[PDB]
Length: 183
Image (cartoon, rainbow, N blue to C red; front, side, top):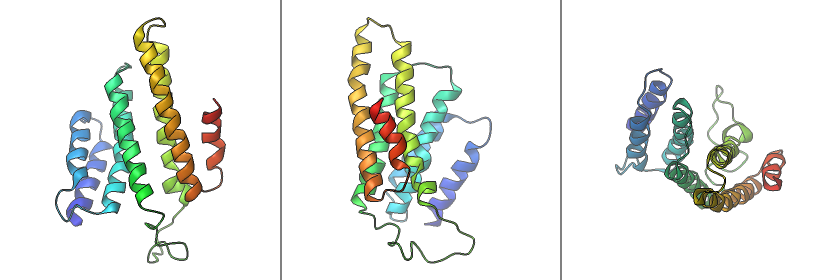
C-alpha cells in the first residue's frame, strides 16, 4: 500500500521538475507497475499506474526534437490497450456502483468525465502523433505503407474505447470519438 502510493507520488512530483531523465522515468514506472510484491498487487494500483504512465511516454517525445519511430508508437498502444483490458475485466465494479462510489469524503470531488474522460485524450494522442509520422515519412517509401497499416489498429482503439464509454459511458463521449471515427 503506502510503499506504492509514496513511490508513485515521488515519481509524479519528480516529473514536475525540469531536469529529468525520461528514459529512466518510464523504466521506473514499468518496474514499479508490475508490483510483483503483494503490497503492490491490486487493480487501483494498476489503473493509477497506467494513468500516469501513458502521458509520461507521450511527454518525453515532445521534449525531444521531433522524429518518427515505429517501435515507440507500438509499445504505448500496448499500454493503452492493457489499461483498457483491465477496465474491461473490471466490469464497472471499481467504483462501488452508483449510490456510493466509495466511502464519502468531504474534501473529495468525483467526476466521471474528469477521471475517466482523460482516457479518450490518450487515444487522440496516438492518432495525432501517428499523423505526424505519415507527414514526415517519404511519400513513396514502403515505410509509409507500413504506417498506413498502423492506421487500422488506431481505428480499433477508437471503437473499443467508444464501447467502454458506452458501458460506463457519459454524455459528450460520443461527439469526439465519433468525429475521429468519421475522419
